[PDB]
Amino acid sequence: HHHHLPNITILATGGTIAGTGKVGVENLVNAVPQLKDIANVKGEQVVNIGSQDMNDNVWLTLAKKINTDCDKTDGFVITHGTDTMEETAYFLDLTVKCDKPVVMVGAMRPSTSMSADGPFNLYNAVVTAADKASANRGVLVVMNDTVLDGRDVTKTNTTDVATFKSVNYGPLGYIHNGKIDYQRTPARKHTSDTPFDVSKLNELPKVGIVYNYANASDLPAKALVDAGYDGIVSAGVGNGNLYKSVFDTLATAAKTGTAVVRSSRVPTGATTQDAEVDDAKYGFVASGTLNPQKARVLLQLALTQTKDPQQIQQIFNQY
Amino acid sequence: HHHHLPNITILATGGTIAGGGDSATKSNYTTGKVGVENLVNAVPQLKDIANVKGEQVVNIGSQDMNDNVWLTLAKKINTDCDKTDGFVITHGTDTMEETAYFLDLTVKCDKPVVMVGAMRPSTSMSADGPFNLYNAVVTAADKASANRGVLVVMNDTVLDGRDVTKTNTTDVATFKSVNYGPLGYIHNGKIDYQRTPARKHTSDTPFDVSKLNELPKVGIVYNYANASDLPAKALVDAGYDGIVSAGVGNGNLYKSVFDTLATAAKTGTAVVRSSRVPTGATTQDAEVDDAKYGFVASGTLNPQKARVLLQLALTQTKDPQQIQQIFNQY
Amino acid sequence: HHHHLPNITILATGGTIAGTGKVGVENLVNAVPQLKDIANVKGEQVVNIGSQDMNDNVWLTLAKKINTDCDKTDGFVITHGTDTMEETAYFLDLTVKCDKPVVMVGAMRPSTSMSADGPFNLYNAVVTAADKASANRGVLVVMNDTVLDGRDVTKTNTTDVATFKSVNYGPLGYIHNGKIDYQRTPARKHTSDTPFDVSKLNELPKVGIVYNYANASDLPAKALVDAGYDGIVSAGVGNGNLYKSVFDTLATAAKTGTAVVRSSRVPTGATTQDAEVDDAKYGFVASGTLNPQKARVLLQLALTQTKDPQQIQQIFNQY
Amino acid sequence: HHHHLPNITILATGGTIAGGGDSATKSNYTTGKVGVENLVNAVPQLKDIANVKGEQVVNIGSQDMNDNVWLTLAKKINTDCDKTDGFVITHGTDTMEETAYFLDLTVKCDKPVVMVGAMRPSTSMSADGPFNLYNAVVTAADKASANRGVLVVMNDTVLDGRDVTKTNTTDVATFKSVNYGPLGYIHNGKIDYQRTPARKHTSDTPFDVSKLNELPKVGIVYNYANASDLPAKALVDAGYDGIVSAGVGNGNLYKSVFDTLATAAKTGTAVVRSSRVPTGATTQDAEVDDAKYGFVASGTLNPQKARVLLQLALTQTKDPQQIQQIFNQY
Ligand SMILES: N[C@@H](CC(=O)O)C(=O)O
Ligand SMILES: N[C@@H](CC(=O)O)C(=O)O
Ligand SMILES: N[C@@H](CC(=O)O)C(=O)O
Ligand SMILES: N[C@@H](CC(=O)O)C(=O)O
């Protein structure tokens, strides 16, 4: 018998954890020599960008690489910027078909700063990826000693190391002394339980986001309609409500080939049916607890399958 | 000596507080439907605490709030300040945080101005509106409420108009001052105030809307992965005075949005970096060199709040350094 | 065919929802005539008390009554004071063997007050008890349009209608328009998956709680030891830490027949092993995310099975 | 003209900030082990911002904090006020909220007094202590910090000593002012203060500990279902000066605890109702008739904080009406 440690692959994309997006994956790994106590780590550099410039091409690269490399490794850690980690995490949650752990991690302070968070965050992300109990929970985010599901996780504060929270349904488990006590798992369908298959796609449907506020301009929504966008997500006020002129434009869009999802600029809670807006009349879809950027992720993937608003609403009710 | 109650004026604007549906249990309803009289008569205890007069200013959902209603309200409060002891504004919850900050910067009346709404319509089981209205009147009637700026009173809490925001789509407890906390809590019709806002408000600002017929055009663009530049270009093509960016993280911009706004700022469009992230400041001295591009950092002002201050800044100046000073003081 | 509504039993115990503990169950039910749209409701008055005077005898009555009456009804709602609802809920979570919904509800404002919360809270508690998806999730608390598990739920604010929160792991689902979208279920073992069986017990082991703070007196802990308590839970400072003189007394207690659990006065997070206290040396048990009052519930039930600290720690790791 | 840095004195008391373990990754450690010099030298940037002098007052876990250390610290700060520009107190996190409020009521020095600790030991990977100490020194050096009472600086946040509390057992972000919010946030070594505490602190209180050798004996009892009266009776039998009840909900007491404390209050023991509930006030005019029993309602003071004010109240008075007035003003 020989004691064996799991093989973990780090897929590096950039971020302040490498600051954004300057230091290579080898350098990050070598800065945390205690990783050798818990895993055999191999690093690959996918891209080296600020996540404020994350895009559809990188999402598709990452999903295809994890799906292709699933059988070569025991788990994955993705180093990423914090700004759009919540978007990438949910894209991968819906398109990764590997049910081995896939864990995303970043840092709110650069590697050079006093009390930098990145080293311990990376250690705990590898702990999570190495834990057999992490499998079959979907794509995870590990930040500030917490395991968060890719669907609900969001950046709640501009600078706090403790910014990442699952604001509607809470975390899956807490990490202490290199161990996780998992008390929850996401009930929405993820990974191999979704129909989304991006293995042959080179691009995704065009989906844009418009913001609502007092005296809102309809010019952004008209610009997306004039460009023939596939979908528009509204960052509505309150329970997904729309300023009158935005409502007029989106009502046109939904009857003229553009899928419309009502989400909310409000940071917690669902955008529901059965409140002030008759979604069925207008052909709109209610986003539930998906915030605008997350609702975009699912609307792009829905539009790979269907343009029918009723079928899109059912997708928004299952994933 | 005889006890006299304060005179409180209710300026009604609509909202779910004035909403109705056909069932106490079904969620479906129409906002901004019931008049101010019906609201007042649903709270018979109000006569214990004030002499209430109701005026219907408009009756709309606050999803359709607009600059004209803002100007009407500021001018009415500043005109009528000497006729009453305090004001309550019944309003929708969806943009209450915007109206409250606009009034906090433009009201010159030293008397309490309190905004209130309801997350459940007037027809619903356990409707929140009646007690919210009672507590708003308590707050407007309390002499300790004066000189604290425009207030929002929701769920037994007195919140400053600058920091207060709607945090949850459905919860009666939605309104929170997420960066600096509430000013006071209300129990049994009494307030223990432990805080007051330090940023300049009301008669300490230079903003005077008494003779304005309209406000500068300021739009908001969202940032996210693969963000389109088409919204930003549409506001620039229309000659907008200002654009507020709902940035990712600490006010960061997707590169194609950054490019459009950098070009606009060079032509004289005012550009404020705010954040889609619901708490925390958009700072200077992070990843964007504001001075180089002619941008302004919003600090703790979220995108819709930063729009309010940017519109008022543009009544005074187009210079980015002067607008940043405004964003550091109000 | 005939459309049939579920049979729901309301077991009334008191509370402000009946204000505390003055109005009878019939009166509460008749104040919400819309209950007839969703259930056939029958009410029984178990006791009529302020939950600040909740006690072991009422817990045992309730567990035996639900276990006995399980086959007569489709679901249970328990009307209760808010002050110790979190304790009763977790006791029932560990001792109820009915896997039909068991839902606890209260009110923060009395029935007579402006904008009283009780009516809609009771409506939503019956919605929850009538929903087939509520089964097999353990004992639930329904407050402020939210379904909360009995283990994690706690009262977070002295007066707020929104006081009840599952502060470590979040809620199970949100209620809108008489429907629940459940996204979570508790992983700790509950109800028919626990060994605790109170069917023949007339009393529970004596377990008391001591508080830690600067310059803490050891007199409370000595008083419980001198009375021969079966167990003591410490409301420790920080990560379950003990003031020196309290530590001295509890170290004695644990070697002299008294089970000692370290919990925390801190409102969120676990009291862990492997920090400053060598639990194994002293024979102490770490409470994890169980706050002092919840740790008391599980320590009483553990002491029905075992007095061995290692077996008590395993119970604290599974339930 | 030449730039001069402020003189800041670090009074070290121990804590996890001074803790050590034998591994950077294992959780096991010992508190209050490393001396103040080693802490200062772990933050080489401190010379950019202050002239730092360290004094080791004690080296203990704050789980073993006590009245003697409180009196030492208050007397030392009040004696040494003219020798320095500001103070930082390195301390354990577990009872930092208690020490901070005691100093907030007894320090008469008008200069900044800032408390700081660390949730991870000095030996741990990504230890929080170094940047926390840097930010504490920033806060103590900032002239805008003065006259705000005793402060706690943790996780880039400036918190008032009255409202601040430890909310989480393990998280670096644990310290929050859960009722009224923080005073300011720290970014790039700068603070934007937007709040100051209204309750009277420091030179505005009557509490003078300059000649005290000890403090009144005040104990804390917990309430829960089937609560034993044995803890309350043990403090009464020992002749305690005061007892604080960690009540259920809005300061309610299990009947047998209520009975013991009602009898004690009649003999002259001071009794404060607080709450085990982590946010919100323990109010008057709820289910307990305080006036009838001779009890005092703690308001937003949690049990350990209410103990601090009760000990100091008992240095001035034993009258329950005067103690309630103290609980309404400080
Ligand atoms: N802008 C950086 C921020 C971070 O990683 O903390 C990024 O998202 O790449
Ligand atoms: N849409 C409504 C929502 C509410 O008031 O709660 C409004 O803002 O007018
Ligand atoms: N003291 C009451 C409080 C409430 O129910 O809100 C009780 O627990 O019975
Ligand atoms: N027990 C330690 C915990 C810490 O400082 O974080 C102390 O309070 O001294």
Image (cartoon, coloured by chain):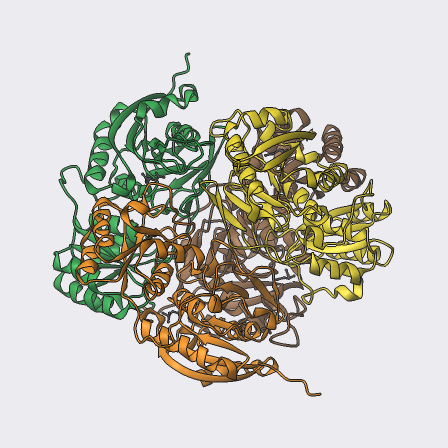
Chain colours: A yellow, B brown, C orange, D green
In which quadrant of the rendered view does residue C129 lie?
A: bottom right
Q: Nearer the viewer, residue A287 or A145?
A: A145
Quarter containing the C terminus of chain C: bottom left
Q: Is residue C170 left or right of residue C252?
A: right
Query: Residue at coordinates 45% horizontally, 70% vertically from top-left?
Result: C107
Q: Position of residue D216 (x, y in %)?
A: 16, 49
Furthest residue to the front? A1
Q: Nearer the viewer, residue B290 or C137?
A: C137
Based on the displayed image, in which of its 4 quarters is residue C61 positioned?
Answer: bottom left
Nearest the camera: B102 or D89?
D89
Quadrant of residue D210 within the rendered picture: top left
User: Of residues D59 and B195, which is closer to you in this image?
Assistant: D59
Across and down, in percent, residue C297 comes to: 36, 64
Q: Is residue A195 visible?
A: yes
Q: Position of residue D169 (x, y in %)?
A: 40, 46
- In this rendering, does residue D105 appear at all? no
Quarter of image, ligand 3 = bottom left
Q: Measured along the vertical axis of the image, is residue D219 above or below residue B28?
A: above
Please indicate whether residue D82 sits to the left or right of residue B203 in the image: left
**Does A196 sit above or below residue D253?**
above
